[PDB]
Image: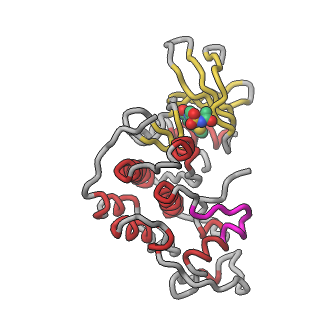
Amino acid sequence: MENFQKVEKIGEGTYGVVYKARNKLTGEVVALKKIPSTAIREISLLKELNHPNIVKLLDVIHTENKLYLVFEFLHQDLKKFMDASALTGIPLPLIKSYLFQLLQGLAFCHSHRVLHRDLKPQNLLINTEGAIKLADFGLARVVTLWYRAPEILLGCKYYSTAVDIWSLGCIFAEMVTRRALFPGDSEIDQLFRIFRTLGTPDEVVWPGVTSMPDYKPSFPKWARQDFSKVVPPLDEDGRSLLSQMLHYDPNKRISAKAALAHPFFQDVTKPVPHL
Ligand SMILES: CC(=O)NS(=O)(=O)c1ccc(N/C=C2\C(=O)Nc3ccc4ncsc4c32)cc1
């Protein structure tokens, strides 16, 4: 760590604090994250999980029982860009570009059996060229519950890649409407917000749901809402895609690879954002 000079704190993340830092032996500006043999080996697998839409893990430094991760630095996160764009809205072509790029990133991770597990606007980083990148991919193997898939909330311990599709669908809806889709402030508030919008799940729409660990037969039974009410003014292609990303049954939920082939992306482009 004597090779790095901290510049500024850029995040109080889930796995540790992140700093903007300067590498004295190359002049490189990086994101330095200050965090057992199992962890060293899993984190070393992530050094090879390289893709243009995944924030690059430059180095892993284990010293004095402390673990530091050296990452590529990007100047803004999607949380800030959404806040800066709240009065006007992110233009649809840019929403579409960001969603497309994030699906490419997830399709890549998922093809290597790597899950993110905690997608949220705070760990989606953007640059001036129009790129968006996923940060903290693989580290999971007040914390926000807003983007949590219902199977996690219902106690599934062996959840799948579908959890990341759910989170990304929540983020897509939030870019379009300029408001979080399900801003729960407890696990039950989170689950009940999901149920009030998408209907209380049952054995018809989600076979096996009633036998999940935290499922309660006493859950209130809410009727489902139309997506035309939930994400106006998103067009029919976008609503169709979103509905497939928010299917209750993780097995029915669209995969990242199938989402990339959805007609919503027929006219996708790569606009440059106003930062
Ligand atoms: C500074 C602030 O609060 N918001 S911001 O200006 O929008 C802003 C600016 C810069 C950043 N970078 C964040 C990171 C970065 O560059 N690589 C990583 C790698 C891992 C990682 N795990 C959590 S975060 C993060 C970053 C974020 C926000």
Image position, residue 114 (x, y; %): 49, 51
Residue at the image point whose x is 61% and y is 76% from the top: 195
In the rendered view, does 69 fall on the left or right side of 252?
A: right
> Residue at point 41% right, 32% down?
128
Q: Position of residue 91 (x, y in %)?
A: 39, 50
Asked if the stretch drawn in magenta spans residue 80, the answer is: no
Q: Decide which of 145, 59 is in the foreground and name it.
A: 145
Establish if 63 lies above or below 177: above
Tag count in the figure? 0
Question: As drawn, is 96 to the left or to the right of 33?
Answer: left
Residue in the image at 41% along x and 67% along y: 254
> Can residue 112 be seen in this snapshot?
no
Question: How is this picture coloured?
Answer: secondary structure
> Eyeballing the image, is 34 above or below 186?
above
Query: Furthest residue to the left?
Result: 266
Name the residue nearer the viewer: 44 or 198.
198
| Closer to the camera in the image, 275 or 264 | 275
Give above or below for 167 relative to 136.
Answer: below
- Ligand 1 is found in which quarter of the picture? top right
Q: Quadrant of residue 3?
A: top right
The quarter of the displayed image where residue 107 is located: bottom left
Is residue 182 magenta-colored? yes
Magenta residues span: 181-191
Please tell me which residue is depicted at 53% across the width and 55% down the height of the picture.
178
Location of the N terminus (image quadrant): top right
Residue 81 visible here: yes
User: In the figure, is residue 193 to the left or right of 188?
Assistant: left
Percent across and percent down for residue 99 are 41, 53
Indicate the position of residue 56 as horizontal and vertical percent values: 47, 34
